[PDB]
Image (spheres, rainbow, N blue to C red):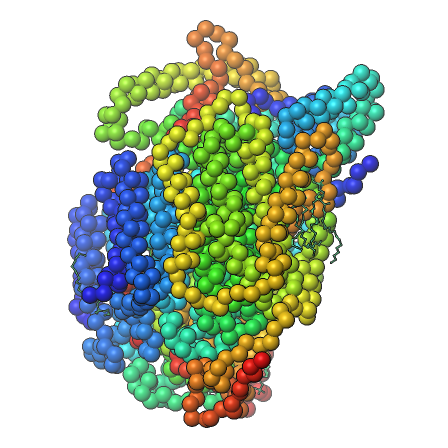
């Protein structure tokens, strides 16, 4: 989510992703902790018996039969964490998230309540206003010609600088706003 | 004068005052949920009086108070039928609603829109009362559609979640399919009986034909989630647990069975529709119990249990025992609502975790929920002298001794075994093992709201069957004499289901693992019915809606035929007429030609 | 009837002599007063009619249409106030003049006692609408839209005129009372078949009938908000009123001449409804829903039974109010977002909750939730169709389901889900917009209390 | 702000206009593939894979997280058909044909067995229920001026 | 060996079962790299427009405009009358009308004949 993606997944990443998926589905099959521990140790032993192999061709022939075997026995109803994309509370609090800019449209009788909050908000706004003019040029000179090659962003390198394109990441609504 | 009518109307009327006050200052404060809860408790206490009057004598009433309109020979008026069914169902619904509101005061404490949520619950209760007390088909349709709209609004409570909106639209779709049959029945009765009033319909229909009864059966199957139109009820578990306990467990989903019960005088004169109802109920209860047997979400297990119980109610209707079906509705209300409250208590205590894989030893960790769920599971399986006994045991006996399908009877017995099996599954995977939840233990039962709300329905699910059965008049011929093995059949199949489920669940501890079989995959994916039927038809509809109706016909061929052809022809004729070089040579040659033609053609 | 006509005419000098900053206030106040005056036409008899003079008469079919026409004008003024802010005073006065002239032409058309007079005003309604569409429309398609809206209409109505004068040379009169009292059967003949077609096609094309409806989406998506309101709420019902009036001289030919249209309607209502399932424009979706409802009205009129006529009248009134409200909601989104695409502005319930409530009520009314008068009309039409043939229920039933789907679709795409992140110019709803929605929706729920007012002369 | 040349156009016939169309839809020319040049007016629009929006990555930082779309990327012709609220094409644990066979077989078997049970019902070893007054002639319908044929019941 | 998964239109192939992801070539890597490059360029453009303090308006998306235009207004100029389009239009626009006409006409003829013979039993049928 936070990390920028690459152009492709290497062989090691694919193997590790299979290992995690297989362990999770084995846990979903083996409900009890001791049974899961036993079969997960067995799966670890099965997984690293080809850990030391050198050639790419058969190492890719493995992890293909492994995917087929996983898809045959994949527990059609695996356990999902409730906040995960398949969980029972995935986007439950999405309706309570309100953008910050809505506060700019409040009535003055509403802003009269919470004066300290809005003073701090004005401070944040002026900080953003200066930092943006710096950030545009920083990104302009830090980018290779022909455009970006990866959607990864640089940090700030000067003293009073801020990381380019920081406002909408720092001012996230919240995980549970209401 | 005769306080019966005044009391019956006052209950429904005072149910509406908090809706009027929803724009007052109380709605903006934190006392509104308690206001609604107190109003519902007062309404329950008031409605207890006409039930006593009917129990003493048998008081029955029709109140046609407001005249709405008159289409020539058809008079439509606001009429209420205060019969046995109404005066028996209103107290039960109000009792369950009071318990659910007290439970929600604890369950939804951190919800910002709890006042709106309480208001929504009261609106559903009002619509359901309108449905239950209606005397004509139009008022019944008003309640029918009101409960559906409230279900749509409460399923999609968290409107930022895509799945909730999908489930709400699914419920609307299936209930609209049932609404087709409802409208068919209304049109038939208006055209043939010249009435939507129930009395004239009963008078003029001594041998009811197939069409109106088939329409009524379609509507009942739609709203009670029978096998053809079943998946929306399990999908409706997207809503908050109080919604699942109130609407989609015990009160709203029995509306189709209630519709079939209201029209029972016409149903007993038709044998084909009775057989259709029997087969539909049997297949529904079997299929839903089979699906429930392998589920891992606890709310899904309870929802499939509700669907199988509704199928059993339809089986009871099919063998011409409507009062037994009403009694089963009343008992199921109690124990199913309490089961859902216990499940919601577990879910809240385990940080909104619903999978039974991640709940272990709760028998000692939270004892009150354990006892309540144990008593509810015993009541659901028809333990003798409990609330579910007095309906389920009689239903099983009646199906055993009747001239009916052998297949439907076998399916009913197998479904009873499967009911015992999934009750065993819930208990075994939620209470008996070692803990399997995250290390930060936040388990807490000590809230008086939760305890009292659960305890009232506990007392109900223990004693209500005895009280109600002993306080109602006999409405059918009993099955006094029976073979000994036939008398014990329900208990025998329940014990066999218990034993087989326990034996199969005890093998999960063995240190052996194997891949699942085809039957398990069929049971886990709900017979693959949601997959195919939610992917093949919808796609083939939507694709057509863009390719043929919109693009090929509307945007191309209808455009080609009238306007484009006219434009093309007129433009070509304009080019033909106006493209002249301006040479008098050709003009005067043409003049000569027309002069000759006029000379030699028009005379 | 002049107690309504003369003040409507006096609206024009009042508009033109008004101050530059007081045109909207005066127009709104006096239009509301004219609506209050026109409310008195609702007192109808079970007997013939309210025959005021030789030129104008009123019926319980004409009275609700007149009340709706007079009520729509203040709402149109309120809706037009916003997007006409930067316009010169003379052009604003011209806009208000076009609206007033349209109201005058409609008022007279509904109450005219002569078929020729009715034809003249029925055509006079075209010029203000065409000017409004092609002058104050926003996109470049408006010109083409206007052309369609014109020629379709004229292509249907030029034969009617011929038929009309022919009738007056045979019966000797085109007065509706005499025509009704001296009606004679139409024999099955080719000449009679073509007379039937000439008398029917002009009203079919303005409903619009399926297959002749191509002008309506263009006109409704290209018009300004007031133009869309008046087109959907009142101008569609002119064809229904005309067919209700003229079918008295077409019997018993209608018994078998109605078959091609009935099919075209019964299948057509399916197609258009399904079209609403795959639409990327809000106004286009609302226009296609209007086409489906008017197909049901066409079926009701062709069935020619008392329940059919009652249902058709009720459905006409209900659809007028509902479609006007839906167009106003879509425009209130458009003036913030300037796109008119459904999936651009999303999750608006979080940012505008009361407007979301208005959206819900409008969608529920379009969905025909009982006891709304939308459902009353739909159910009466469905019962009459079932008596006509029991198989019709199938198609009718299907339509019902589909309608709900797309209605809720429109509610879910725009109001639910997550808000669009980059759209940061969604301001709080103004009192004007909320009042507009309230003044749309309160009359519907009030009318459900006295449905006899909108059930027509066969009640 | 979109120019006239940035709109969809007619079917590309030459590689140069093919490459021009690919650049207009922000995609590689190797990945660009228009609809077949049939009658229907797809025209210049690109034919993207028929995968649903539900099978897109949920852990990516989409600009539109609910639709799982990115600003500027080409939109599938049938996006409104696949919006996670509608038909999805995600892979299933069991193959489509196997699911269809199993569901159809279960339904057909249940129908056949219900018909078999209709032919072979279940009942108890009893005779018909007996009712006193000419099988309740007067109380069931009536017609008290016809003197029905008397039916007398057998005491055993 | 295990039973094979068979993909379909409505149940597509898993990415982990694609042989195309196991046939890695330098050209494939270059294609992936340039696809990521164009995605990164579009993301940078959007995020520059999105984080700008000065901007106070909906960001215009050319892709969305192209989608709506192609779905609505680019249809007819690219329409060509072909045997396939002609046949499909004739079927989908004419066949249903005549099918429903036949069904309804047969039903009404049956009802009319029954009424004329008097054997229909329309008792209590007062409202129509
Ligand atoms: C008349 C005499 C009366 C006396 C009768 C005899 C008394 C009783 C004798 C007992 C007989 C059997 C009872 C045991 C039940 C089976 C248990 C079992 O072994 O399951 C494990 C075993 C494999 O499971 P697994 O892969 O290891 O699961 C992985 C983990 O265990 C995952 O585990 P988990 O933790 O996730 O969940 C465990 C769950 C998961 O288990 C499952 O997968 C569920 C599947 C098994 C239960 C299904 C039973 C319901 C049967 C209804 C069938 C109706 C017709 C449908 C037709 C289908 C057509 C396609 O299992 C359970 O919860 C318990 C299962 C049920 C036990 C409790 C009730 C059983 C008794 C009730 C039935 C008989 C008494 C009725 C009383 C009335 C008196 C007659 O399941 C099977 O192999 C199925 C066995 C039987 C299925 C027959 C259907 C095959 C159809 C193939 C096609 C044939 C040709 C058709 C052609 C048609 C052409 C049109
Ligand atoms: C039911 C009995 C009620 C008795 C008490 C009095 C009720 C007065 C109702 C007045 C008429 C509706 C007014 C609509 C405009 C609302 C304006 C507004 O923004 O209020 C905000 C205000 C302040 O809230 P807020 O904090 O600004 O809200 C923030 C957000 O906007 C959040 O806002 P929200 O989430 O609170 O949204 C408002 C809320 C409620 O808002 C609405 O939905 C309003 C529209 C509901 C109906 C939609 C059309 C359906 C066809 C109705 C045709 C019958 C009309 C009857 C005559 C009406 C005369 C006006 O949404 C809903 O709860 C969904 C309603 C679904 C109703 C489904 C069932 C409808 C048929 C029920 C049967 C009726 C006949 C029974 C016949 C047999 C027995 C006699 O809250 C309210 O006032 C809500 C009022 C409670 C809803 C009343 C629903 C029942 C009344 C239906 C019509 C009158 C029936 C009279 C006979 C009753 C027996
Ligand atoms: C395009 C989008 C839709 C627009 C609206 C469409 C609605 C208009 C449809 C016109 C309604 C039908 C017109 C005539 C119906 C009369 C019945 C007759 O046609 O059927 C048979 C007639 O047989 C044949 O039809 C003869 C005529 C055949 C030639 C007509 C052309 C057929 C198709 C043309 C369709 C073109 C429509 C669009 C024009 C641009 C009956 O046999 P018969 O008993 O002997 O005649 C009875 C009539 N009598 C008593 C006067 C003698
Ligand atoms: C409240 C506080 C005020 C207390 C003072 C009043 C105390 C009671 C005195 C009332 C006097 C009697 C009265 O109300 O007048 C009768 C009058 C009826 O007028 P009639 O002409 O006689 O009949 C209708 C046909 N024209 O009754 C009433 O209007 C009041 C009672 C109406 C019932 C409540 C209506 C609620 C439902 C709203 C309509 C919903 C849609 C319709 C659904 C139809 C279903 C088939
Ligand atoms: C016998 C004669 C019958 C006469 C029928 C009269 C039909 C009335 C419309 C005639 C318009 C014909 C002219 C025309 O459309 O030209 C094509 C024109 C070219 O554009 P221009 O503006 O001329 O040039 C722009 C570039 N500088 O294309 C268009 O714009 C078409 C838009 C107008 C069509 C609108 C709809 C008209 C057809 C609707 C159906 C009614 C047909 C009436 C007759 C049908 C038979 C009963
Ligand atoms: C009759 C219905 C004919 C088909 C109607 C097609 C309508 C297409 C438009 C619907 C809009 C698309 C849509 O709703 O999305 C599909 C949506 C999403 O699927 P989920 O599984 O919930 O996914 C959530 C988790 N990701 O699913 C649905 O809601 C679609 C449901 C369609 C049901 C069609 C099958 C109905 C068959 C009825 C047969 C039974 C007849 C009656 C039997 C009773 C006997 C008296
Ligand atoms: C949206 C576009 C729709 C375009 C309009 C479609 C309707 C066309 C209706 C026919 C047009 C002419 C109507 C005639 C006016 C009525 C007068 C009448 O009925 O008198 C008849 C005359 O009837 C005719 O002459 C009509 C002949 C038709 C000539 C014009 C052809 C127009 C096109 C015909 C086919 C299309 C009609 C349906 C189109 C469907 C919609 C596209 C009797 O004449 P007499 O000789 O005095 O009496 C006989 C005993 N001696």
The structure residue drawn at horizontal position 50% and vertical position 79%, both measured from the top left corner, is D131
Q: Using the image, determine if residue C59 lies above or below residue E122.
A: above
- Residue B511 can be seen, yes or no: yes
Where's the N terminus of chain B, which quadrant?
A: bottom left
Residue located farthest toward the top when viewing the structure as drawn: A159
Q: Is residue B373 left or right of residue B428?
A: left
**Which x, y percent locates residue A110?**
25, 29
The image shows residue B73 at horizontal and vertical percentages of: 33, 78
Q: Residue at x 25, y 79 (%)?
A: C46
In the picture, residue A84 is in which quadrant?
top right
Name the residue nearer the viewer: B576 or C146. C146
Residue toward you, C188 or B44? B44
Q: How many marks?
A: 0
Viewer can see residue C267? no
C265 or B360, which lies in front?
A: B360
Image: C66 above or below C180: above
Residue drawn 47% across the image and 54% down it: B253
Q: Residue furthest bottom?
A: D146
Locate residue C418, reporting x and y percent: 46, 36
Residue in view at x 66 percent, y 55 percent: D39
For the C terminus of chain B, the quadrant is bottom right
Q: Position of residue B225 (x, y in %)?
A: 53, 55
């Amino acid at each position: 989510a936070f990390s920028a993606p690459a152009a492709y997944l290497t062989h090691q990443q694919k193997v590790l992703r299979l290992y995690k998926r297989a362990l999770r589905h084995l846990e979903s099959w083996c409900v009890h902790r001791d049974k899961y521990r036993y079969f997960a140790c067995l799966m670890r032993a099965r997984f690293d018996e080809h850990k030391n192999e050198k050639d790419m061709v058969k190492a890719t022939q493995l992890l293909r039969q492994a995917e087929e075997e996983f898809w045959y026995g994949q527990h059609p109803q695996p356990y999902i964490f409730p906040e995960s994309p398949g969980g029972t509370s995935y986007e439950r609090y999405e309706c309570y998230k309100v953008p910050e800019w809505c506060l700019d449209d409040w009535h003055p009788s509403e802003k009269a309540m919470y004066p300290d909050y809005f003073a701090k908000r004005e401070q944040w706004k002026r900080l953003r206003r200066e930092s943006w003019e710096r950030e545009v040029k920083q990104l302009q000179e830090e980018t290779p010609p022909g455009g970006p090659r990866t959607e990864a962003l640089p940090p700030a390198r000067k003293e009073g600088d801020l990381p380019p394109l920081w406002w909408h990441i720092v001012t996230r609504p919240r995980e549970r706003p209401m | 004068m005769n306080p019966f009518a005044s009391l019956t109307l006052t209950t429904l009327t005072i149910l509406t005052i908090p809706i009027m006050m929803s724009n007052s200052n109380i709605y903006k404060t934190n006392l509104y949920p308690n206001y609604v809860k107190t109003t519902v408790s007062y309404a329950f206490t008031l409605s207890l009086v006409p039930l006593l009057m009917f129990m003493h004598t048998g008081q029955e009433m029709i109140i046609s108070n407001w005249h709405w309109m008159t289409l020539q020979t058809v008079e439509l008026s606001l009429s209420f039928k205060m019969d046995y069914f109404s005066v028996m169902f209103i107290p039960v619904a109000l009792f369950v609603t009071w318990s659910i509101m007290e439970f929600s005061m604890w369950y939804m404490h951190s919800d910002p829109f709890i006042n709106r949520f309480f208001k929504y619950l009261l609106l559903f209760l009002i619509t359901m009362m309108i449905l239950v007390t209606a005397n004509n088909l139009f008022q019944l349709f008003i309640g029918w559609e009101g409960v559906g709209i409230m279900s749509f609004l409460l399923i999609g409570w968290w409107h930022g979640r895509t799945d909730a909106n999908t489930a709400a639209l699914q419920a609307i779709l299936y209930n609209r399919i049932g609404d087709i049959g409802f409208v068919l029945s209304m049109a038939w009765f208006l055209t043939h009986s010249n009435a939507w009033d129930l009395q004239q319909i009963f008078m003029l229909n001594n041998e009811c034909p197939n069409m109106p009864l088939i329409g009524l059966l379609l509507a009942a199957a739609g709203k009670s989630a029978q096998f053809g139109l079943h998946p929306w009820l399990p999908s409706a578990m997207e809503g908050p647990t109080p919604v699942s306990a109130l609407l989609h467990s015990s009160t709203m989903v029995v509306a189709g069975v209630f519709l079939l019960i209201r029209f029972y005088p016409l149903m007993e004169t038709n044998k084909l529709v009775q057989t259709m109802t029997l087969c539909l109920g049997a297949i529904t209860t079997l299929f839903t119990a089979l699906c429930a047997i392998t589920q891992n979400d606890i709310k899904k297990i309870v929802a499939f249990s509700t669907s199988s119980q509704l199928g059993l109610m339809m089986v009871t209707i099919g063998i011409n025992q409507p009062h037994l079906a009403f009694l089963h509705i009343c008992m199921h209300a109690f124990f199913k609502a309490m089961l859902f409250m216990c499940s919601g208590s577990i879910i809240h205590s385990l940080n909104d975790e619903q999978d039974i894989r991640k709940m272990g030893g709760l028998y000692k960790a939270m004892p009150f929920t354990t006892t309540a769920l144990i008593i509810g599971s015993l009541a659901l399986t028809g333990m003798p002298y409990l609330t579910g006994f007095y309906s389920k045991d009689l239903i099983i006996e009646a199906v055993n001794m009747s001239y009916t399908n052998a297949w439907a009877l076998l399916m009913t017995l197998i479904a009873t075994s499967l009911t015992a099996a999934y009750s065993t599954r819930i208990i075994f995977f939620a209470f008996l093992g070692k803990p399997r939840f995250p290390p930060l233990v936040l388990i807490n039962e000590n809230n008086p709201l939760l305890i009292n709300s659960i305890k009232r329905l506990l007392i109900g699910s223990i004693f209500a069957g005895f009280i109600i059965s002993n306080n109602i008049p006999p409405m059918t011929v009993p099955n006094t004499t029976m073979p000994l093995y036939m008398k014990m059949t329900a208990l025998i199949v329940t014990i066999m289901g218990f034993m087989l489920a326990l034996e199969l669940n005890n093998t999960t501890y063995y240190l052996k693992f194997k891949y699942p079989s085809q039957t398990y995959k069929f049971s886990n994916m709900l017979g693959y019915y949601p997959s195919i039927m939610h992917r093949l038809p919808t796609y083939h509809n939507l694709s057509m809606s863009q390719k043929s109706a919109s693009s090929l016909l509307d945007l191309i061929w209808l455009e080609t035929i009238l306007p484009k052809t006219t434009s093309f022809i007129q433009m070509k004729m304009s080019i033909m007429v106006s493209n002249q070089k301006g040479l008098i040579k050709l003009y005067f040659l043409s003049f000569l030609i027309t002069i000759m033609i006029s000379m030699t053609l028009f005379n | 009837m002049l107690k309504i006509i003369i003040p409507t005419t006096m609206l024009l000098p009042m508009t033109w002599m008004s101050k530059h900053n007081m045109i909207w206030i005066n127009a709104t106040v006096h239009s509301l007063l004219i609506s209050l005056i026109s409310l008195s036409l609702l007192n109808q008899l079970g007997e013939n009619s309210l025959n005021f003079s030789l030129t104008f008469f009123s019926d319980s079919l004409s009275a609700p249409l007149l009340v709706l026409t007079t009520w729509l004008l203040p709402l149109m003024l309120m809706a037009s106030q916003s997007h006409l802010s930067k316009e010169t005073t003379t052009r604003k006065k011209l806009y208000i003049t076009m609206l007033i002239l349209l109201q005058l032409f409609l008022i007279m058309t509904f109450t005219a006692t002569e078929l020729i007079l009715f034809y003249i005003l029925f055509e006079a309604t075209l010029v203000p609408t065409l000017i409004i569409i092609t002058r104050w429309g926003n996109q470049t398609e408006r010109l083409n839209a206007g052309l369609y809206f014109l020629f379709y209409t004229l292509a249907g109505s030029l034969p009617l005129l011929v038929a009309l004068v022919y009738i007056q040379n045979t019966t000797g009169s085109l007065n509706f009372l005499i025509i009704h009292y001296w009606s004679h059967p139409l024999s099955n003949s080719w000449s009679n078949i073509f007379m039937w077609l000439a008398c029917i096609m002009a009203f079919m094309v303005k409903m619009p009938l399926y297959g002749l409806h191509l002008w309506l989406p263009k006109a409704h998506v290209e018009a300004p908000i007031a133009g869309s309101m008046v087109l959907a709420a009142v101008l569609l019902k002119l064809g229904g009123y005309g067919m209700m009036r003229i079918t008295t001289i077409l019997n018993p030919l209608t018994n078998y001449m109605a078959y091609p249209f009935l099919m075209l309607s019964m299948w057509g209502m399916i197609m258009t409804s399904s079209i609403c399932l795959r639409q990327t424009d809000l106004k286009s979706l609302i226009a296609y829903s209007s086409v489906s409802h008017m197909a049901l009205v066409i079926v009701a009129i062709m069935i020619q039974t008392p329940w059919s006529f009652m249902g058709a009248t009720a459905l006409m009134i209900a659809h007028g109010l509902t479609s006007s409200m839906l167009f106003c909601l879509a425009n209130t989104n458009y003036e913030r977002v300037h796109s008119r695409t459904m999936i651009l502005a999303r999750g608006l319930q979080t940012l505008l909750p009361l407007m979301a409530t208005w959206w819900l009520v409008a969608s529920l009314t379009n969905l025909a939730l009982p006891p709304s008068i939308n459902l009353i009309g739909e159910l009466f039409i469905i019962t009459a169709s079932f008596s006509w043939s029991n198989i019709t229920i199938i198609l009718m039933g299907m339509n019902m389901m589909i309608t709900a789907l797309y209605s809720l679709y429109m509610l879910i795409t725009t109001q639910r889900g997550k808000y669009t992140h980059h759209i940061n110019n969604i301001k709080p709803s103004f009192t004007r917009e909320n009042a507009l929605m309230a003044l749309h929706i309160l009359p519907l729920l009030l009318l459900t209390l006295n449905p006899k007012m909108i059930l027509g002369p066969l009640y | 702000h979109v120019t006239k040349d940035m709109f969809p156009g007619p079917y590309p016939k030459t590689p140069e206009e093919r490459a021009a169309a690919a650049k207009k839809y922000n995609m590689r020319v190797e990945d660009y593939e228009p609809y077949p040049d049939d009658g229907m007016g797809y025209g210049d629009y690109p034919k993207l894979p028929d995968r649903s929006q539900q099978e897109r990555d949920p852990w990516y930082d989409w600009d539109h997280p609910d639709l799982r779309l990115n600003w500027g990327e080409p939109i599938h012709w049938d996006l409104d058909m696949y919006i996670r609220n509608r038909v999805d094409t995600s892979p299933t644990p069991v193959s489509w044909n196997t699911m269809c066979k199993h569901l159809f077989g279960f339904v057909a078997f249940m129908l056949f067995m219900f018909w078999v049970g209709e032919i072979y019902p279940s009942y108890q070893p009893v005779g018909p229920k007996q009712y006193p007054y000419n099988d309740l002639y007067l109380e069931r319908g009536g017609d008290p001026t016809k003197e029905p044929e008397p039916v007398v019941h057998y005491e055993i | 060996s295990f039973p094979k998964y068979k993909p379909s239109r409505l149940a597509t192939l898993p990415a982990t079962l694609d042989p195309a992801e196991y046939d890695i070539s330098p050209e494939t890597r270059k294609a992936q790299a340039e696809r990521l490059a164009i995605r990164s360029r579009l993301k940078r453009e959007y995020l520059l427009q999105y984080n700008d303090p000065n901007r106070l308006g909906v960001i215009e998306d050319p892709a969305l405009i192209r989608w709506t235009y192609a779905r609505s207004a680019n249809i007819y100029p690219n329409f060509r009358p072909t045997p396939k389009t002609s046949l499909l239009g004739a079927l989908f626009g004419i066949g249903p009308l005549f099918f429903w006409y036949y069904v309804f006409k047969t039903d009404r003829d049956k009802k009319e004949k029954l009424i004329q013979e008097g054997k229909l039993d329309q008792t209590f049928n007062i409202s129509y």
